Amino acid sequence: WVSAADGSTDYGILQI
Amino acid sequence: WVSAADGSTDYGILQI
Amino acid sequence: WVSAAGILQI
Amino acid sequence: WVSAAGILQI
Amino acid sequence: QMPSLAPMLEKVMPSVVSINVEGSTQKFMALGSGVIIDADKGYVVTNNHVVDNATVIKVQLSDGRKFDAKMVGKDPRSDIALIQIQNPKNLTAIKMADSDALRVGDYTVAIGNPFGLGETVTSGIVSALGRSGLNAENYENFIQTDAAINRGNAGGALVNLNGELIGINTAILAPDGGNIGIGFAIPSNMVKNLTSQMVEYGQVKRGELGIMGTELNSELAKAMKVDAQRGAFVSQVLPNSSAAKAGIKAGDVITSLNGKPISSFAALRAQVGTMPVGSKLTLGLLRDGKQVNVNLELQQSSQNQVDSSSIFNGIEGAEMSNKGKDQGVVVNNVKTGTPAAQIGLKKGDVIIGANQQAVKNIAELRKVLDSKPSVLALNIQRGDSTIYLLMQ
Amino acid sequence: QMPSLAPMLEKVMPSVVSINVEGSTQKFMALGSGVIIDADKGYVVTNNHVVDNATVIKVQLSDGRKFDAKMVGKDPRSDIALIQIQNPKNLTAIKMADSDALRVGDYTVAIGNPFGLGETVTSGIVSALGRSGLNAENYENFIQTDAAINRGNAGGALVNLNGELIGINTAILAPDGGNIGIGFAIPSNMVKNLTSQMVEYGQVKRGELGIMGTELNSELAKAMKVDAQRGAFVSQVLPNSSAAKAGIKAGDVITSLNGKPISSFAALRAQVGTMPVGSKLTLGLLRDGKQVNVNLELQQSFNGIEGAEMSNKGKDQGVVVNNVKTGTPAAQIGLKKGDVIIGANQQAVKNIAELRKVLDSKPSVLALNIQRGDSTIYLLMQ
Amino acid sequence: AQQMPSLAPMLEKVMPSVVSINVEQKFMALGSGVIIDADKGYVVTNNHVVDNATVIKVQLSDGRKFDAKMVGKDPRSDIALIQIQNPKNLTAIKMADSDALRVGDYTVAIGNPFGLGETVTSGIVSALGRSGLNAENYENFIQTDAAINRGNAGGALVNLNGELIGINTAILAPDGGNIGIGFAIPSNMVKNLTSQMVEYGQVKRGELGIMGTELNSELAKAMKVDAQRGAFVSQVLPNSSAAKAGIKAGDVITSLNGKPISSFAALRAQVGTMPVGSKLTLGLLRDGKQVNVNLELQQSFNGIEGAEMSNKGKDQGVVVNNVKTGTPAAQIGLKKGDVIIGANQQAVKNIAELRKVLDSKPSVLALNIQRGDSTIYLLMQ
């Protein structure tokens, strides 16, 4: 995958 | 269970 | 090898 | 690593 | 002032959608890409292997809008499928270019949904043309490109600098499931032909010249005293076939189609395999070091006419076609270890009727499937015996 | 006469350096890239994950010259760190462009040190913008590019055809540890904002709107009777938060930030997450199919000490405690509201000035002579 | 209606110039090659593509097959040259001066990845003078992000004008799949190596006879030198071209025939491909003063099987002058001073009579040599 060099499906609730 | 003392779901084709 | 993302007849 | 497809002397 | 693809892309990108699919064969989930062919009808082309065995199909536009889509046609042999957006509102279709104008070196831009990240654009060039051999049973006349293509790009668009569709990205050559600069896309012309049929018939009416053959290599050229080291070698012509009537004899080497040179037998197969029945075309032959031209017309293939997955939507491994004159649907050939043979189906069977409804041709049969009954009972006949085959 | 990036590159390449690092967590060795932001001060920006837990940091220029660098600032949440070249001599800085001008399709050039090979240049295009989700806790508004990026490129420069820095190459999506045409870089603007703080403060003063929310998909749009199929959906606003004070109500959908449209909630999170505390900004909201505009000011998460807020009492009558927090270490040592600090460590406390003058002495233990009611007690610390 | 930019125009002319090579404990391999001389049917490729090859067949872009025979090979530089048998109607490629290349220049790779067929990919010059993949090899690689995989080896790397700038040789891939880092040998080095193979069948390798190491920033500080890159002269061997030229230790070489030097490893690779006796000029830096010097590469009777001998007096046998230890000569006993009196019961007065015995090609060779006042025999095969 990526490597350094219930409720809406798109996301749980994040804080801004 | 029991112990001695595609196509219709009810069964594959048996011969009489 | 390749992955999705003899005499032949024409 | 790399694959085909100290004092040195000149 | 800097050069950029942005100007061209902002017009074209809305035309590329991403497809989400749910199915069963054991539930599975898959995703890919598609291209809006008809903004009005909401027609969207894509790879057959993306929407195969699909119970639910949802399309998500570039602006984020979601829709539901229903299958329209599918052709496993060419890996091209056509779906239709339900309730099409304010769409943008793409303009197709003539793939026959492509030349190795032309610049290409790939648009798709890699790993579901979203609409992703990458660029590159035409690496090669007429590539084939990934699956000898499929009609493949691939365009090759070094433009970045990964899982999800399938059904995506491959366009030129003018934003015109030149191909549909289908597969890649990657030992690690990650792009290494070798991607393949189905020529736009092939898509043009295949989809236009699906729009009218729901399937493809497969025509043929009725000739057996193989790739013309340098070795075979030596044996046959032939100049060309590449082309389609005619092993034999079937009796009563368009080719026969045209005057094609065995030992001939086909070099061109409608003027356009032939890369290989596999390419020719793919070319005509997409053309509609009755299409009048011309071939360039080479017999005895002698250039020959011939006028042909595609016909109705008597044998191996139509796959079964095209009628049962999920049942592969059995080819079948109409029999004589409204005499039912005979099965031409059956592959072992396939969903079809799993229910009993064997070569030589002739479907007389289904669910107490008479079946004379494929139209009648499909007519019964349109009813979508819970269980299907086929009244086929093997030899002089009459039997039934049950489904679901 | 052939087209070439060479003319542009010879100008820009000196500005890109390669970073070698030695650390411990068990000694380790790592390497990546960096970009000179201030030729004179010797400021070099890079990925926090390249210089994290570093005991020794050495920078090598394009001409081969080596220098030693010292940490200036670091921000794990955004994966941006800033170092400073020691004894900066004859350096070349890069000009930064406004990443808000980028458009999918623009040509990009990557510069870095893949596998320590040395300064290596690759090209590509802007695949996509505002990509995020690699780490839901990080502030990420990545630029996506098909330009060749591998381990080592991190902290390297991503520039446009004019040699202007548009982003800082950070991560790639690779199942095999090798580039497959999917690379991510932190937008230049975000680097502009984050670094400028580290230069000034040594860290980033983080301001939040104090709102909960999630991605606005088509489904959720149907339920909330909303038009936009994308944006930031406000689940709730925290009390006493800038957003609350601004007039932002739950169920609202944010569509723009300072005029610029919003790609996603994750993007918006990354945007403001890089802006300094007190930054005044404006949002575009959508409530009940009506366009709304609001002015905001970022917020932090008399005199207050150790999570305890106090003030002066009358005229040199000590430091009275106004109100205390329970979860804070203040109430964990006994401190309650209404207390009046008469003195500390055998020193008389008339005001917050004399109190702080004792704390300047930095005693191992702090003994407060407060008074609750008509009683005189003590509180100890450390 | 409009007009698009394309490589097609350039490629349709160049592509015939690139062929694909098929090669046969038996093994089978495939790669690519470039037609250097349309007329003679000379094709360059990677030495590791045609190494240990019993059968070599070349397939053109139009599909035509030919048989090829080895002409020359140089493992140290991984360059090999073959020749098409019965060359008919071929197309050769024009070479460009790789010394003009600059990081940023656009590149196009042509080869046969996975035997798919002639495949074209593009990119840019990522870097120049890359080396270190094999310290014993002469490598001055060009680096490019152009798609290169298994099969591309021996393939062509050209500029927008369809001129050969390098020969794709290797890639840096952890998974055996291209990741944007490919290496190609500069056209100039190919120019020099092939031209020798055409005339000699091998490369007569010359040396300046100097010891040295990479000039880094640290070392520059100690030696009070300006340049942060180049070849640092550790010492010059006595009786070497360099010595005769006036090169002293502590010197820093900065240029070769005018062309600046990226590194010691590059310089080593440069002269390593030049024929013996090649006259060249170097740019040195001693005590912050620019110096120029004119040089001539050097080499490190009859010799048989790794053993060098001559005649003795007048028909007094074939005396051995000096032997090599690692060679098969000393592996059969031969040491310096020995005097072959005869072989296989045939008198040997000189190298002419000795060779007349070898012309008989006996299954076993019995040498009647003489050490000191003793007479001994040595056997072979």
Image: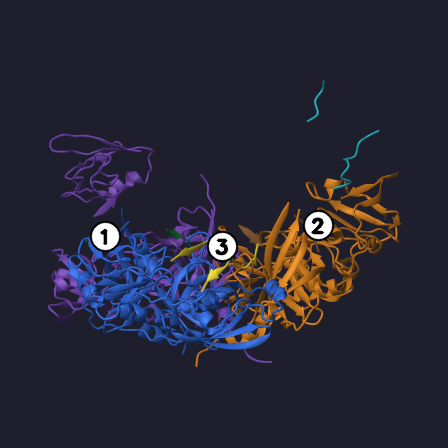
Chain colours: A yellow, B cyan, C brown, D green, E orange, F blue, G purple
**Looking at the image, which is closer to me, F286 or G326?**
F286
Q: How far apart are marks 3 and 1 (CA)?
A: 62 Å
In what element is the residue under mark 2?
Answer: loop
* Front: mark 2 or 1: 1
Residue E236 relative to residue G250: left or right: right
Q: What amino acid does circle 3 point to? A: Gly
Residue G59: x, y in percent?
Answer: 51, 57
Question: Which chain does the residue under circle 1 lie in?
Answer: F
Point out the residue furthest to the top here: B5
The kind of residue tagged 1 is Leu
Q: Position of residue E383 (x, y in %)?
A: 85, 39
> What residue is shown with label 1?
F380
Q: In this view, does F187 lie to the left or right of G119?
A: left
Q: Which residue is tagged 3?
A: E178
In this rendering, would F312 be left or right of E195? Answer: left
In this rendering, which labeled residue sits more in front, label 2 or label 3? 2
Which residue is nearer to you in this view: G170 or G52? G170
Q: How crowded is mark 1: few (under 14 residues within 10 Å), some or many (20 or more)?
A: few
Mark 3: which secondary structure? loop
Residue denoted by label 2: E314
| N-terminal-most mark, 2 or 3 | 3
Q: Mark 3 lies on which chain?
A: E
Q: Find the distance from the CA under tag 2 to the CA under tag 3.
A: 28 Å
Say yes or no: labels 2 and 1 on the same chain. no
